[PDB]
Image (spheres, grey):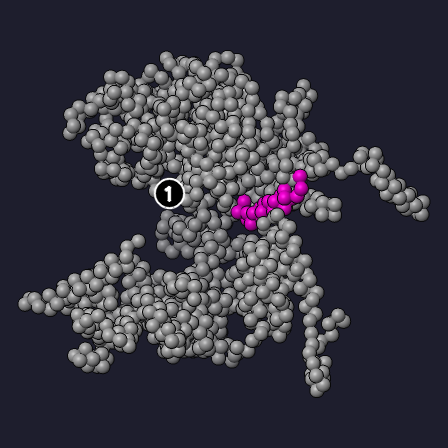
Amino acid sequence: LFKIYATEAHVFPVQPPFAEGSDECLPKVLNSNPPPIIKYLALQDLMLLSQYSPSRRQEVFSLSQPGGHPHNWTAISRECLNLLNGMTQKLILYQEAAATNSVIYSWIQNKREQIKNFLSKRVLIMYFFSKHPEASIQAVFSDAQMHIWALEGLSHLVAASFTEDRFGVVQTTLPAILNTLLTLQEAVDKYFKLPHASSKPPRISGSLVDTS
Amino acid sequence: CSLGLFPPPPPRGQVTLYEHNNELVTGSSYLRSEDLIAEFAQVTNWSSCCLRVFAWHPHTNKFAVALLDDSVRVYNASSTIVPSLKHRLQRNVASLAWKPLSASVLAVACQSCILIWTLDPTSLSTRPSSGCAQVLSHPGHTPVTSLAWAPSGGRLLSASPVDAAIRVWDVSTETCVPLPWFRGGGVTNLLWSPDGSKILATTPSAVFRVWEAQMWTCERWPTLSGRCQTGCWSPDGSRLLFTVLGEPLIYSLSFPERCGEGKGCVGGAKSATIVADLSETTIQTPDGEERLGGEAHSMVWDPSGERLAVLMKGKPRVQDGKPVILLFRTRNSPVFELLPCGIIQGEPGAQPQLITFHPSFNKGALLSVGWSTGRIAHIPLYF
Amino acid sequence: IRDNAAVDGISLHLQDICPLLYSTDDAICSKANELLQRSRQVQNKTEKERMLRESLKEYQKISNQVDLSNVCAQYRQVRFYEGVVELSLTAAEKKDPQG
Amino acid sequence: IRDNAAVDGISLHLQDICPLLYSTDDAICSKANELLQRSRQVQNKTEKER
Amino acid sequence: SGAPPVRSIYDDISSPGLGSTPLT
Amino acid sequence: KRAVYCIIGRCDVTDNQSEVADKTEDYLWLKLNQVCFDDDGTSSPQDRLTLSQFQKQLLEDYGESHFTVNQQPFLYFQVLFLTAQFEAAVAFLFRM
Amino acid sequence: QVDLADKLLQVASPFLEPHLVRMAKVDQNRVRYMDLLWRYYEKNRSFSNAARVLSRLADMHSTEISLQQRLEYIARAILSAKSSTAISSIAADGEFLHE
Amino acid sequence: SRPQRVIEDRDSQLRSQARTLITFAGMIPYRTSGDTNARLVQMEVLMN
Amino acid sequence: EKIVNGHLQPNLVDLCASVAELDDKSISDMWTMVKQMTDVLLTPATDALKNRSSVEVRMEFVRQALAYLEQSYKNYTLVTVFGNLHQAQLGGVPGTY
């Protein structure tokens, strides 16, 4: 029941009907970096509205009077670009971390690591310390559902702007979108050529706990 | 429209080569899990035809063909090399579906599974490795009759007449999501609308169900004399055409857009119109009487929505019980219209076995026809 | 060579008396070879082509002193016919820089 | 002027239908004002000075 | 009568191009 | 309707299309599409502009005072360089 | 040297014509370079130069196949002169036409 | 995939037929135009 | 230095034109124009007068001069439309039409 109610959708207005509730408007809900269930719900709404409601894409492409600026699009696209570049660097730093395979406190650090380098030399203890490939790869992508929703919500808005963007507002960031998507696809297609990065994990079908 | 408004078929042995000016130009040439597929297959004689399925790639001059030996082949305008696909689970191929927003992915429906072949578009070898073939299946969902991808590329559907649940799949997280309904029949065929928001699902019974891809809701149509046999969406998805076994009719049903919030309801108008009449008529020709009318087994629309091709089958009183191709001109705004264009004739002594349009032919439309000779033809319609 | 001194003045001073000069390209040839032999292990086509266009740009400095027969045979060994055209022109271009 | 239309495309329509003699200085003042209010939005300095 | 005009495509633009901006 | 025909048919070299060509670029563009290089003796010479006639026309039959060189030097450089008079364009640009 | 003549006749490059116009004066296999040169001129539509080199395969060294071949060559020299005067009205290609 | 002589056969026949038409135009006792006669010559000039 | 150290000959147009990625925008369009007029697939002859007298190369100079003047007027039509969008009514369809 909790897992149904806490993974049911939410809807966030993009443009505010009243000024107080504007904290809960989608551009502000994304950029304010709220508790992660809200940032997941907000990107799940962004990945729904961008296919299944044209008026809510038109809330994103709007210019905010009096000052004429596309604050809704430029706040939404900027935070999707923050997360996509964050994943590009998260993939690079793991590929590097795979190519690389007062006095009391520093004395404790030295003794801790002198102990690591005596415990690793004992097979029965190395057997517990080991860097699991499947689990460490699954730790890199452990948050990837957030990044899939930023990616599909943005690429649906960049598809719909071709008939809904009366202001060219999405076209102004299209070069930066294509650069960040292609450098991310490069980071993915550098990473996926690593040992165990190509292989699929074994699954049980119809378990009550899921493994997605 | 009605059949008593068509021009005559061309004189017996002329082949229709193309449409131009809206004229059809001619020349002198160009159950078990087996029999339950034969009850619902898209090919008008699937149990004896050499060709079991045809499918274009949704963006490119590439196509997949399933054959009576349970090969699937791939052909492409930029490749003389033809990949021959056969897996250790591949048997009685019923349907084919290429993935949109990809070059590299083809789905295949079999007697015991779905097969998702991955194909390297720059390395189209004559027989790719049996590892390049991701297997999907679930208990009770066998045989698989039909397959349909979402336009946005992120979801796949599958049908089985044994199974009171559409199976939605994500091929990438490798998940299986049954949509179980409270009886009636199982699933026979499946069709998305082009927006990817609406889905038709047919059954073995006098009931169809339409579904919503947003909140996964269902709307129910149990109001037919026979089974719903076939249908097609308009390019906007606002219109759905359908036919019923025993009824010589093309029906239409409308779906307005969600100018209103907060309720997952599939949203169709309460009841269907009739828009074409396929009753058992005569037409006069230079070769005497000819006779038409029967039941519509397949219908396919062009990407532009201006040509509807209809694969009829005559009753055993009209043309010996042959299948026939009718071509209609269509309009989708402001009114929905069906107008005649004409009747498509092939190689003398052949029968039309399957029809479908090309998805990216930038000169009106292009109709693929599979014939009982085992031949494929491609008839352009220039507009 | 080792201590990175320019040699033109010691060549001419050596040529009242008898003999020859030069290499220094040993370090660049070693680097070009470090890339070329890893191109035989790299499965990643785009990065095999990267490390070959890097290996080539080390050899393209030193194209007067390279065993071009062996390097272009070692390119054939990896199907890098692109570097066989490029390096063999850069190895004529500098042997007759006057025409 | 607010919605950044050009006032030539309303002054010359007023001038057929307002004082039927030499309706002129209303339109000159309106255009002088349009250029002045557009100068409040122009960020290129030499063109603001134009 | 026959002669070139003496003007570039930028005169009746007054402030043209990608330059004349103080920072990126 | 004149200008599009004078271009596509390489004719009326003595019309400048001055109701349609706003600037010196548009005189250059009109006359450069009107250019032939080819001795088709079916062409009447009153329709026949060669590049070499157009080169002379700018350098000698109009000259540096026609383009107001002291005020628009880059426009006269554009006139010579887009007629491939590169040596004259350099011996102009190396004065000022 | 590898019998790739169709692919020599795929190189659009200026150097090819001065090369054949050297070899047709210098190699003892002179006939092969005249044969490449008329095929180059016909393919490039310099038919006057093709005819004015096909003569230089019928100037030969030992006789052609009959007076009936001489009569097509005379009528093709006539055609080549009537090609010349109809493009450049030089008196010499009209003097040589009567001849 | 002919013998090359069954292409040599056809270049020479078309040259001979083209000349047969030009010689005939030069023997007609009626004013054909300078343009129709020049077009005829130009057609074997572009078969030379 | 690249010639002296034997390297591949660089494009001198890009070395010189990067001095015009600084201040004077008219010198920046002058170098853009010079670059579009040196974008020529020259016959690698040992004679500049024969290359400059070629019919093919003189067609190429005019083919490039027309392409420059056309992209110049394409920049003018772009800037004029993007300054005046409320008159221009550009909508949401890309292409020169």
Displayed quadrant of residue B364: top left
Q: Tell me: residue A111, above or below residue D32.
A: above
Q: Can residue A93 be seen by looking at this rendering? A: no
Q: Residue furthest left?
A: H29
| Residue nearest the viewer, comparing B139 with B314 | B139
- Residue visible at 36% across and 24% down in the picture: B48
Q: Secondary structure at mark 1?
A: loop
Q: Residue B359 location, x and y as percent? A: 41, 37
Kindly give the residue lying farthest to the front in the view shown: G62
Instruction: Inspect the image, locate mark 1, and give the three-letter code of the amino acid beneath it.
Output: Asn
The residue singled out by tag 1 in the image is B362
C22 sits left or right of B80 in the view: right
Work out whether residue C73 can be spotted. Answer: yes
Prevailing secondary structure of the magenta residues: helix
Q: Is residue C29 magenta?
A: no
Residue range (magenta): A170-196
Residue B175, how many percent across, how many down?
59, 27
The quarter of the image holding the N terminus of chain C is bottom right
Question: Is residue A184 magenta-colored?
Answer: yes
Q: Residue at the location (51% across, 80% down)? A: F95
Classify B329 as above or below A118: above
